[PDB]
Length: 306
Ligand code: HEM
Ligand SMILES: [Ca+2]
Ligand SMILES: [Ca+2]
Image (cartoon, rainbow, N blue to C red):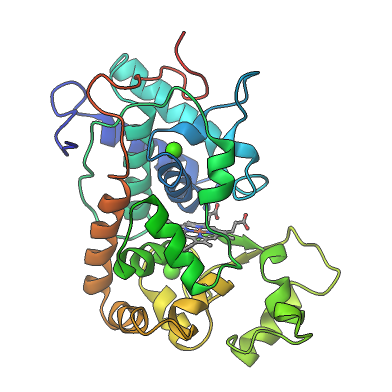
């Protein structure tokens, strides 16, 4: 079983080294905290949190970095390399990349103003990467609520609270115009914008993402506090200001009878949201981990030990 004290003897300063690395990177890249949290999410949804997403291509298996949900989107890999090297220097062959990324995600959330907690540890690193599984398991912004629920249940998260709380990760970070073009100009082949998108915000988004414009242009997930980890994400949903389809469906989908009350509860209380986020984060971090002697303690997160 995973435990928060796993490295209290072998590498007591691991969390501090991770924090220091992120603090330093944030000065030149204010988006890195969001990027790191997302890497952990994409790691856990594919064969569990086993650092499989960090592996680069080999002639025997393809990298998950080329998955539809990661390609030209996932980022921060060199930063993970930096903290890994620092931890390896402080504590040789001790901290797995899987655990490192989990701590990095928690520290990223805390540094951005979110809750502070000690994540369960003891995960080990995968011996391969899973591109096909990543293409099948990572949810997409155009998913309906039933599809979002299916995606979470598929990896082991059955609770609507899991889905609603973890979606709160969109309280910060960036999103490409590419992913909302349909909502802005032609939703579900209706030739009209998504009716669940606030019409005033629709105008603003159309200005940032004009038709035939730069699809790679970036827009903030949270128009209220773009880089702060808080519950504003839910207040936006209540006003039909969720940025992507999957965000707004939590509040507007015909199948949202169970998610609406959660959205409201999280928008009404920061404490309720933070508590739910920590709970959901630990549940996600507990998805099919390799433990004990299974897998390895990867020295270079990009390659399997030889
Ligand atoms: C519920 C289904 C979800 C969908 C469909 C989804 C979809 C997306 C999309 C389309 C982007 C934009 C990528 C880009 O434009 O390059 C993104 C970014 C992001 N997502 Fe999600 N996401 C989901 C859940 C989550 C969860 C569970 C977390 C973490 C707890 C998370 C954290 C983030 C963060 C922080 C960013 C910004 C990353 C950055 O700016 O580098 N997402 N997501
Ligand atoms: Ca994984
Ligand atoms: Ca925010």
